[PDB]
Structure formats: C-alpha cells, structure tokens
Image (cartoon, rainbow, N blue to C red):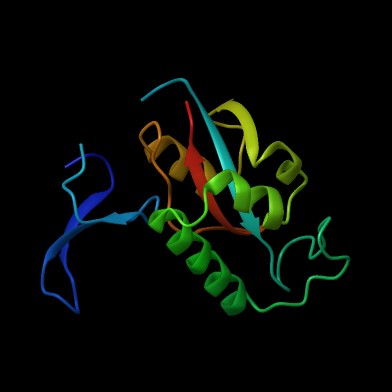
Length: 145
C-alpha cells in the first residue's frame, strides 16, 4: 500500500475501504516523492485559529467542532459532484487565496506548516485530502500538480 494508506472495514456496511492517516482521505477503491507539488485548499477557521479573522468575517466565532462539520459538508458536496472544489473555495475559504480559487502555487518541503506539507506530498496528482488540521484551522487540500 502507498505511503500512509491502511485497510479498514466500514462500520455501517461491513465493506472494506482504505484510509490514509496522513491526508485523512478515505475511499472504497484500493489506492494506487516529487521535489515540489502544487495545491489548492479551502480553509475553515474557528475561534482557536492563530488569527481568528478572515475576509469573510472580522471575528470568527465558530467552534472547532462547527468548523469540522462545515469541512465535512464541503467534502460531501465535492465528492458527490454537487459542487466543485474551486467554487466552494472561492466562496467559503477563510483565506485570501479564495480569490485564486484556493490555489497556493507550487512549493517544496520546508515552506508550509508541517501537517499541511505532509498531507500535500502524500496526495497523488488530482487527489483530495480529508480534513487537515493546522494552527490556522481546518483545510481541504487538492493536489493539482
């Protein structure tokens, strides 16, 4: 299994699935290092974020638990195809990168916060993370290159 992936059993259906503890990605299908990757992200901040403020809200008051529920709902809509990642990032990311549809550009190791970096480099091109936690808040990460 690729780096970070483990086999688990679904609690509701009993079907095997795969989980990546680095990216917090999960999927039914069996899954299958570059100097630099390019990623987009969608950040939801919460009251304990290092700077609890964004272009969306001067004072961010939602709890960390409420932020996770928002992230979970965005992931659901992205995976169902009801929304695409870029449209949600443009509307709802608590980050100036929302204006760039979440794009952060390319980066190598040693430049981003560690949980974000580790998840970014564990994704395959085109793959999306689950909720990734940093001092900024909770991220959904899309590796684009």
